[PDB]
Image (cartoon, coloured by chain):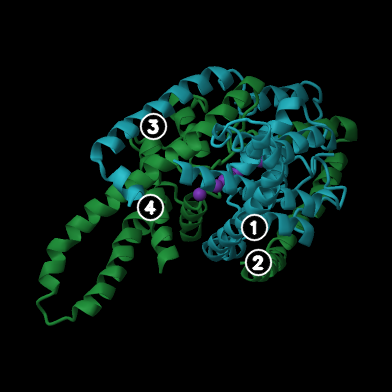
Chain colours: A cyan, B green
Amino acid sequence: GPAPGRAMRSTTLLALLALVLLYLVSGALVFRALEQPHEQQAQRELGEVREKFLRAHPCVSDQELGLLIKEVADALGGGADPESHSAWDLGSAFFFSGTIITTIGYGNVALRTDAGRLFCIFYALVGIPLFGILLAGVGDRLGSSLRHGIGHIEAIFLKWHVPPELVRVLSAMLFLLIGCLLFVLTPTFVFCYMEDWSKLEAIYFVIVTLTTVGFGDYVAGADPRQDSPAYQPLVSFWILLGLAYFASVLTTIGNWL
Amino acid sequence: RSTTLLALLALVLLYLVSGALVFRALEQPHEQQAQRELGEVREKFLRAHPCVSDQELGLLIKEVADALGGGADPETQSSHSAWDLGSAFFFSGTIITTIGYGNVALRTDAGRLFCIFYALVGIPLFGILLAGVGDRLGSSLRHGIGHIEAIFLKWHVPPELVRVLSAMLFLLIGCLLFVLTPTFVFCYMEDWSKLEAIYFVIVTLTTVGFGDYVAGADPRQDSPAYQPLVSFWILLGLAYFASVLTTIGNW
Ligand SMILES: [K+]
Ligand SMILES: [K+]
Ligand SMILES: [K+]
Ligand SMILES: [K+]
Ligand SMILES: [K+]
Ligand SMILES: [K+]
């Protein structure tokens, strides 16, 4: 009814369209000044690296070095450690499978085979939607489990003569802030040391992860090697519950709108 | 229902295992193969030049690793900006669509902090327009078929089956304009293989966005339309492929 109806009005879209278009333009102008100074430090920057090895070592020709770069190119282009770290063992392959259905897709360990790409194609067409079924399912019992809990302490708020305005003015904020505590503030200060990131990196990782954006610029566990069996299912378990609570909030306020 | 959930949970969990098993078989050879062959080139170049120590080589192989990771082209030796307004505009399209290629990673803390607030706002905001377009796109499209549909209902074809016929044609002309045509273009303009043009589109459409393949990211192809017009298709491609998923949930 309202979902197509509010969009059925052509003026609502085209105004929102130009809004989004210029919302993208504004973000591009900001993103430019924030990052343009420091990105392409590789294309021409390696050019000085070659000479600083042609100068540093007269014993090596440029063509010998040119082949060396081309040799290590196909080496790095398939899996090479600049120094066990197998990125396709069942542990990490399970992680890679999860990034597909969650639509996170870090791509930090991309597919090489034309057989693996085809397998992933059908794996995504079927795997992704049925994952959302379970995620929306968990959110049903998860949201109810909080409200069971939300209700118990709610009794105390109303008794202390804070008006029926309490809801809807309070029980929404405390409901989200406890989730903001458990699935954002708690993991960040954990990940701030568990991966030894800075303050913003832990927060930046969580958001891009939970928003299913998944740049792949930040997993850093393995930062060098996965190391511990703690993180492996638990973080995916955190992502799962992170998405579930994320789903609960977007759905509940969907009703309130 | 807790009965369907916990049962589906084991179904989903094993679906990941079954996927991880086959993924291992199709990738563990190729990745670990190069890991062994890298040690060869380390030896092979330590042989050719005893003048160069391994530590001085260890720095270099990491420098070229830092370079190649940055997308440094090993082809010739020595402008096409990445954070130019045209591609930075496309970069914003990666977050709000939750595609997030990550091919051009961020670096500045100010850029990441601004991206934090920009992502939280833009993503549900985009979904409103996307679904909004998908409603109007589906409506304007459904408006067009009716002309042809009126002719089809004369050949004594049962209206019960006329229902099913259009349902096929709905997705067929839909994928034709948003799967076949994009892949045939990507297989041509990017000269990717058939399994790379399809692979790019699908991973992009489902917003998985591995970033390994990105159309228009190729610095050379300077056809004036290609850079943002693909993203224009991405919008319509997202809206259509998502609107079907809603009707999929119904049927
Ligand atoms: K996504
Ligand atoms: K990515
Ligand atoms: K990379
Ligand atoms: K989505
Ligand atoms: K993604
Ligand atoms: K991604």
Q: Are marks 2 and 4 in contact (CB under 8 Å)?
A: no
- Which residue matches tag 4? B182
> SS class of the residue under badge 1?
helix
Marks 3/2: CA–CA distance: 40 Å
Label 4 CB sits under 8 Å from any ligand 5 atom: no
Marks 1/2: CA–CA distance: 8 Å
- Which residue matches tag 2? B2
Specify whether residue A77 is in view.
no
Q: Residue at x 25, y 53 (%)?
A: B139
Marks 4/1: CA–CA distance: 41 Å
- Which residue matches tag 1? A141
Q: Left or right: A190 with respect to A93? A: right
Q: Are marks 1 and 2 in contact (CB under 8 Å)?
A: yes
Position of residue B104 measured from the top left corner of the image (x, y, whole percent): 58, 34
Q: Nearer the viewer, residue A115 or A77?
A: A115
Q: Which circle, 1 or 3, is nearer the viewer?
A: 1
Q: Nearer the viewer, residue B91 or A74?
A: B91
- The kind of residue on which mark 1 rests is Arg
Local crowd size for mark 1, using a 10 Å CA cut-off: few (<14), some (14–19), many (≥20): some
Q: Are marks 4 and 3 in contact (CB under 8 Å)?
A: no
Marks 1/3: CA–CA distance: 35 Å
Q: Chain of mark 4?
A: B
Position of residue B152 measured from the top left corner of the image (x, y, whole percent): 14, 73
Q: Chain of mark 2?
A: B
- The kind of residue on which mark 3 rests is Val
Q: Are marks 3 and 2 in contact (CB under 8 Å)?
A: no
- Which residue matches tag 3? A20
